[PDB]
Amino acid sequence: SIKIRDFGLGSDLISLTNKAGVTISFTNLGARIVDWQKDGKHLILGFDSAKEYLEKDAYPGATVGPTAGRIKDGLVKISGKDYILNQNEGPQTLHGGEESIHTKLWTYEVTDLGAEVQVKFSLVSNDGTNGYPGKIEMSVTHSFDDDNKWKIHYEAISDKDTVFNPTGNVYFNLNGDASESVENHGLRLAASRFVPLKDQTEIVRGDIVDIKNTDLDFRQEKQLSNAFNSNMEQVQLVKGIDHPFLLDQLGLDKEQARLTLDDTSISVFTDQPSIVIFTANFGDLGTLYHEKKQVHHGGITFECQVSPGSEQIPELGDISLKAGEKYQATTIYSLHTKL
Amino acid sequence: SIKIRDFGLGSDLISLTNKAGVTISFTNLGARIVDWQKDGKHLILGFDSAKEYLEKDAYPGATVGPTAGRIKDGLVKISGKDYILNQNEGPQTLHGGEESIHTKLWTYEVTDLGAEVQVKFSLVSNDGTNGYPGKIEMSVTHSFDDDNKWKIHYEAISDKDTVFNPTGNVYFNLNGDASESVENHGLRLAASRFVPLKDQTEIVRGDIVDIKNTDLDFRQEKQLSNAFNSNMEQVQLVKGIDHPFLLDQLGLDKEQARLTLDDTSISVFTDQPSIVIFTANFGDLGTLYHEKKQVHHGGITFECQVSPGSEQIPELGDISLKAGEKYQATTIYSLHTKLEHHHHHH
Ligand SMILES: OC[C@H]1O[C@@H](O)[C@H](O)[C@@H](O)[C@H]1O
Ligand SMILES: OC[C@H]1O[C@@H](O)[C@H](O)[C@@H](O)[C@H]1O
Ligand code: NA
């Protein structure tokens, strides 16, 4: 079933219930996922109205871009030329700059295919918006099916050479309550290397490091508390995890990561080369979700994209988008329940 | 009463009915007016869904900007610096460039004051959008009261020195049918001068001309047919009117324009110095409005703003906006019945 309702400030909340009784909901404010629940438990973090996102934290569950992550000094080179993007975190451009696409109301259309329902959100980033060349016509389609698969497919076309590497910013918490750390979840992740951060500014350090046999090696399932209790300087630096992991084998058919808590597990599939993992290292901030005060480590992301820092480490990839070329990306989060 | 429902594509339709039974409606797609009816008759042009605006003509009834009108070659001078804006009509920048504010979904909040209801729409134009320095935090409040006044209040603040001069693009047609020409309406307009256009590109010619006693003189009420039938160079140039008229006396207190048909009148008040009048000179295009093919001259706008061309005719004004300075503008359209005797035949 599909239900559309007012979510506040003119935004809509679109809720989809599949044959299994699982409910997932989105909002056009930021082409974002708001909730995902089973047997009455939330599996992700989210708010109860549009105002909350705007007042508390506008990133959770949203589509972030045009470039996801931090860009050192807000600088990118396009066709050999230097362009300075909007700087909103000190001199860095984080998540596309201030007032970016996650804070805009996108238009959308719903398509019911029966076993699957799609919600296609669209937005135009005008040429020059926050320093980025354009215009870029973007669309993000979130879909949910009867097999409990939530898929995000992105597409974009630019009138001029530009940069483009968006991501989805859902935070999972299988405890179903923000006041509870995810340290009890088990994580598996098909990555043997990671990108260390330079310092507290969180820009990349410059190198690529092998994590095999370290506290960050999750090639074999392991509980998060391990990483959390590690003394690796990278863990200590951010007080948790806030880093890009390089996937060993690329392709949409491979389960790249798996998050498990008891009988409930989430599998991640993507066609992107990296997953940025951030464990809500918010200290005592205590943001409130559903009346529950969030705890440090009260959530975890799987941001699939090209690793941030390619401006300094080209080996990471190239986020250039040439005029007239069509950008495509796909990420899937699959829900499973043991029986 | 206030009612809200989906209008299509994620936009909503906000419908207000005042105590006199007059209803008016808006959409957050472009902070725009959709309809205004009295006794089951449409007083303005509009479509029945959001998609129609996007597929037929996205300007009607919209808030347009950041700069309304045409800027020659897209070039503006901001604090000694030259900036080139998005050019979407040949080398011209028309109504803020392509995919401008009229095409975005604005957020909104409704405030019920009893005798008055306000719908405040908000949007942020990011710095660099379409070449404009910003960011610019904008708000447009549309309000309707028990006295039949529809008021538009604009506010804006920029982080950077920029330019700002938006307007409202409503089109009236008191026939209530787009397929009926407005040449049968009577027009009174308190303006003695106008700004001629250079040519078909529609940029300003460079001079200001006195129109007293010509077919464009509406200081004293006359039927629109007088202008439409005129062979004056400017009218032939655009096949109707599409020009800025300079108000003779400024201030929100004065009735600057009055549009009448039979027993109904619309009066125009504004704090702006000019009114751009465009009479839907679309020829045979025939866009469908409520299944009626629109006729050439099937509509008339009263875009109140600083006249276009100040880039070339400094005397027209200055639309610059300094960083941190609060922009404000107010325009009001009021509806009356039996304000005067208007009984003609066409
Ligand atoms: O969503 C907010 C978070 O987003 C992550 O991508 C980022 O690395 C974190 O440091 C934090 O900013
Ligand atoms: O279609 C909207 C109209 O807006 C008027 O301001 C302009 O002068 C007309 O030529 C036309 O562009
Ligand atoms: Na809505």
Image: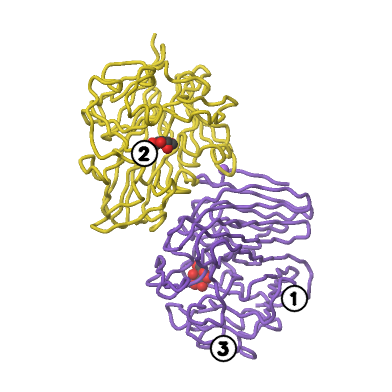
Chain colours: A yellow, B purple
Ligand 1: which quarter? top left
- Say which residue appears at 64% left-offset and 72% top-offset: B272
Disc 1 and disc 2 on one polypeptide chain: no
Q: Chain of mark 1?
A: B
- Distance from the alpha carbon under mark 3 to that under mark 2: 62 Å
SS assignment at label 1: loop
Disc 1 and disc 3 on one polypeptide chain: yes
Name the residue tied to disc 2.
A202
Estimate how packed mark 1 is, as few (under 14), some (14 to 19) or many (20 or more) residues with alpha carbons within 10 Å. some
- Distance from the alpha carbon under mark 1 to that under mark 2: 72 Å
Give above or below for B225 relative to B106: below
Name the amino acid, label 1: His
Disc 3 and disc 2 on one polypeptide chain: no
Distance from mark 2 CB to nearest ligand 1 atom below 8 Å: yes
Name the residue tied to disc 3.
B209
The location of residue A4, given as percent across then percent down, is: 54, 35
Quadrant in which residue A202 is drawn: top left
Distance from mark 1 CB to nearest ligand 2 atom below 8 Å: no
Name the amino acid, label 2: Glu
